[PDB]
Amino acid sequence: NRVDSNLGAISSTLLVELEGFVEQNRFQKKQAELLAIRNEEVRRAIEDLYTLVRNYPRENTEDVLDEKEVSLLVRHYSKNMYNAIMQCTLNSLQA
Amino acid sequence: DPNNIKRSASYVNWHPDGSVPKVVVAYSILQFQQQPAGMPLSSYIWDVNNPNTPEYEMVPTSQICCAKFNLKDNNLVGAGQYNGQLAYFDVRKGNGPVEATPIDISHRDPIYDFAWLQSKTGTECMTVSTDGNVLWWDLRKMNECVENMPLKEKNSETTVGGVCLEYDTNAGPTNFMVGTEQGQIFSCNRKAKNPVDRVKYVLSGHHGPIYGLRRNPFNSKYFLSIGDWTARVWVEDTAVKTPILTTKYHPTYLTGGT
Amino acid sequence: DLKDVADLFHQYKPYSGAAYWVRGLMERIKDPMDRLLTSELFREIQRTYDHLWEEMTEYRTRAVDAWCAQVAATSDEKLPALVRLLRETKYFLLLETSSAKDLFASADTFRQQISALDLICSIYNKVQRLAVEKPLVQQKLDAVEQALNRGLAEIDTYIKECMELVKDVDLVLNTIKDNVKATQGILFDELNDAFNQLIQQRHSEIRDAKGAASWRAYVDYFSNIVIDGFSA
């Protein structure tokens, strides 16, 4: 939900709606904050996910540290799925 | 938000109209020898349309608890504190007290309440403390104690606490219970058809510091007692001073539900 | 569920939340022994019941010993801590009806909590109490009453010092009268505007009574403010 009810609604938006077209400018202010708002929580959410996986007793983990580079891969998948959002929104818009 | 740090949320109330998903929340710390040397508290209003940085922030002059709302409207909000000092806030200013209910003689004690009466075409309130003196305040015009009765037990140990009081789901002529924390639910009516002494019920039988009280809705009047680590269901008759559907003796001392 | 109680007890083993922890679980466990005893397993249940019920009473006993010591010592220092100890005395006092000099002193510092809520008025008054007030403060002799409070700062002495505070609050009303005169000096038809400015200046001058120099300085600041506002 927190990482894919956002990122399947961020890619569901429609920026330009239906001279006076300056209202569109005003309209495209509003939803901008929308995506920004949503993005922050996902940058929050994935982040919080890491803390959950780290802070836990598991007595057979206090001699084996968690690795790093695949957590950077989890982070990277989060980035690229943001990108897939925005390119879907832009292409639907231009259509 | 990352300011919601080192501050236990000791209530959450919900906004009363239908399709406004806002929540009013309420963050504190008791056992005040570890009163936090950092943040003086300020509660919040979040929305679910976006997990917005708190729409409005209410800044009190002391540790907000128990912060109920104003009934069925998108305007106004109450609060409690730790002095005894109630509070009151409107929505078109993200600031301190709109009308801070002042200090007068009696109520100088921590308040776990800001409970509304059905005073029609207006607004109203009452409180409760670890002194007893449940002390009604004014309506709309706010600064005076209306029916300021320090209540008293029949055999004169008037330091009788309370939490989480419940009213009537049948039109509400002032019949209510007070969740008295020493293990004995109390009850009242305020219209003393008798003399001023009108605390009928001590429902002794629940255990230790009680934390739950709620009438049941959707058909009837059976009230609940989820306060200590047994979760009962009680009933209101003068012959049934004992549960009905007692449920499990639990682990992990109970603290609250509905 | 005797071992659920024993697990919860010795794992999670105000101040008086501890005695409530004890006597909650204890009268809680008192009801089952009554319920059973209205014999082979009953001997081992008699073992656990014995010491577990028995040492937990040991903890409540030493708890009242230790916090009789703590109330005694904090009381001695008093002659935070106050809110804790008055809440504690109320709470095991509630328990023990369900020392005498100590409770007398509690009533005394509650009826002096009246004047301890007058100390807070006095300290507010110190907070909002001044370039305008430089004249009066340069002429005022409030330091004599301040020195009376300072000799008080290190029985009925407290009461007479409360009446001294009342007189000082009257001097605070004098400070806020200085503030009010400052605020009213803050705020063809040229005759009407000149008359309004002269009326404000006359009100300030009448409401006044180095002092002459400061009055001239305030009048000059008024003239500068009038030139700033009337040139627009």
Image (spheres, rainbow, N blue to C red):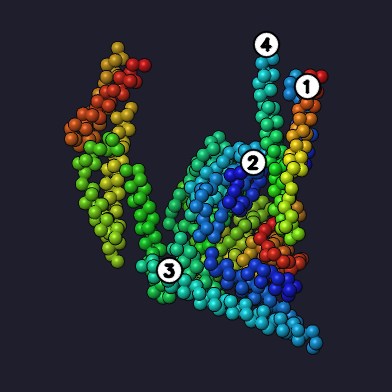
Q: Which amino acid lies under the numbered mark 2 shown in the image of this protein?
A: Trp
Q: CA distance from mark 2 to mark 4?
A: 37 Å
Query: Which numbered tag is attached to residue B46?
Result: 2
Q: CA distance from mark 3 to mark 4?
A: 78 Å
- Quarter containing the C terminus of chain C: top left
Q: Is residue C124 visible?
A: yes
Image quadrant assignment for residue C16: bottom right
Q: Write down the residue under mark 3.
A: C74
Front label number (3 vs 4)? 3
Please tell me whether residue B20 is drawn above or below residue C42 in the rendered image: above
x and y percentages locating residue B113 in the rendered image: 57, 54
Q: Write down the residue under mark 4.
A: A19
Circles 3 and 2: CB atoms closer than 8 Å: no
Q: CA distance from mark 1 to mark 3?
A: 73 Å
Specify few, some or many for label 1: CA neighbours under 10 Å numbering under 14, 14-19, or 20 or more: few
Q: Depth check: C231 or A76 in front? A: A76
Return the chain for callout 3.
C
Front label number (1 vs 2)? 1
Helix, strand or loop at label 4? It is loop
Query: Which numbered tag is attached to residue A93?
Result: 1
- Quarter containing the N terminus of chain C: bottom right
Looking at the rendered structure, whether the residues under marks 4 and 1 are on a common chain is answered as: yes
Return the chain for callout 2.
B
Q: Residue at x 29, y 15 (%)?
A: C190
Q: Which amino acid lies under the numbered mark 1 shown in the image of this protein?
A: Leu
Looking at the rendered structure, whether the residues under marks 3 and 2 are on a common chain is answered as: no
Q: Depth check: B181 or C33 in front? A: C33
Q: Residue at x 28, y 26 (%)?
A: C222
